[PDB]
Every structure is written in C-alpha cells, then in structure tokens.
Image (cartoon, helix red, strand yellow):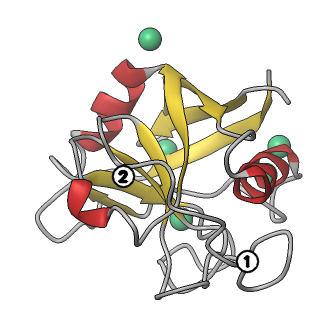
Amino acid sequence: QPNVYFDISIDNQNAGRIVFKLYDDVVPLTAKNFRELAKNPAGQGYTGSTFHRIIPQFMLQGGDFTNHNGTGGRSIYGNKFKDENFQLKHTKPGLLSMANAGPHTNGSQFFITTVVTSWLDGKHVVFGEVVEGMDVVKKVEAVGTQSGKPSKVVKITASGTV
Ligand SMILES: [K+]
Ligand code: NA
Ligand code: NA
Ligand code: NA
Ligand code: NA
C-alpha cells in the first residue's frame, strides 16, 4: 500500500509536501483509516482541513475535518475504532500517532511528533513516520504557541497517495 502525502500551506502560502510511510504490517486498520481519509475528497477527509493545534517541542495535531478545532472528525469505520496494539513506541521525532479520548476511541485526529514522546507509549497507537518533508514539519511547528493555537493558519491543501 502506497505512501501518503499532504501538501501544506501556511498563511495561505505553499510550504511544501510531507510524505508518510504507514506501518500497515503492524497496524493495518489504523494505517488504512489514515490513508483512505487522505485519498478522500475535501469535506470527507484530510484534504482542505487544518493542523489546528501545534505545540513546539511536542507535536503538530490535525485531522479534525468536521469541526476544525479538536472536537470533531470520524474514522472510516465510524466515530471510534479500537486501539489495534501498542507494539510501536514513540521513539523519535517525525512519528504519526493517533489522538484519542481514552482506550478504543480513535477517530480521524492524529499528531506528528517533533521530539521523543515516550510517555505516550501504550496509550496512543503509532502507525507511521515522515519519510520526506521533515523541513515542512519544522516550518509548521514554528507557528505553534504555548496555547497550541497556531499563529498562522496551516492547511492541508491536497492529500492522497504517491
Ligand atoms: K484527497
Ligand atoms: Na494556510
Ligand atoms: Na481528504
Ligand atoms: Na484539524
Ligand atoms: Na526531506
């Protein structure tokens, strides 16, 4: 199954492309959900949504494509799907992990780590890593703030598989 890309704008200016390799062999349903949400048309997935919460030296969070503020989103399976396993750990920057509201509540929201976050191990499912565009991840992280409210709008202007 192919890698996933997001094209990113910051303050409505193109900032480049992030490409992710997903760990389908280990968390196939978690990988499948993020890949189909990336392929979907605007309004039905990541295309046209924002990184609504960004905290430097911690992570960039996105995937709320229904409310744009952290209260929304839904997986391709419905509102919530299970934690498949916690075999992969938050061992390095640039990992994709699911946000949730406790055990077995994954939806569409995810975050990309920018530091080692090993205190999340066993509570958030890691399912992929950035393989191109850590430069772009840096630039998005630079508009984060103490409150997590981005100081410039960061949009996924296109997404799909490459
Ligand atoms: K798309
Ligand atoms: Na933008
Ligand atoms: Na989409
Ligand atoms: Na979002
Ligand atoms: Na790169």
Counting from the top left corner in percent of width and height, residue 155 is at: 54, 47
Counting from the top left corner in percent of width and height, residue 94 is at: 38, 34
Q: Residue at x 49, y 29 (%)?
A: 130
Relative depth, front residue between 100 and 156: 100
| Mark 2 within 8 Å of ligand 4, using the beta carbon | no
Quadrant location of ligand 5?
top left
Q: Can residue 151 be seen here?
A: no
Q: Which mark is residue 74?
A: 1
Q: Mark 2 highlights which residue?
A: 60
100 on left or right of 137 = right
Q: Residue furthest front?
A: 87
Q: Can residue 3 be seen here?
A: yes
Label 1 Cα neighbours within 10 Å, binned few <14 / some 14-19 / many ≥20:
many
Q: Quadrant of residue 77?
A: bottom right
Q: Residue at x 83, y 82 (%)?
A: 78
| Mark 1 within 8 Å of ligand 4, using the beta carbon | no
Q: CA distance from mark 2 to mark 1?
A: 18 Å
Counting from the top left corner in percent of width and height, residue 29 is at: 79, 58
Q: Quadrant of the C terminus?
A: top right
Q: Amino acid at mark 2?
A: Leu
Relative depth, front residue between 94 and 104: 104
Q: Secondary structure at mark 1?
A: loop
For residue 74, above or below residue 29: below
Q: Residue at x 59, y 64 (%)?
A: 85
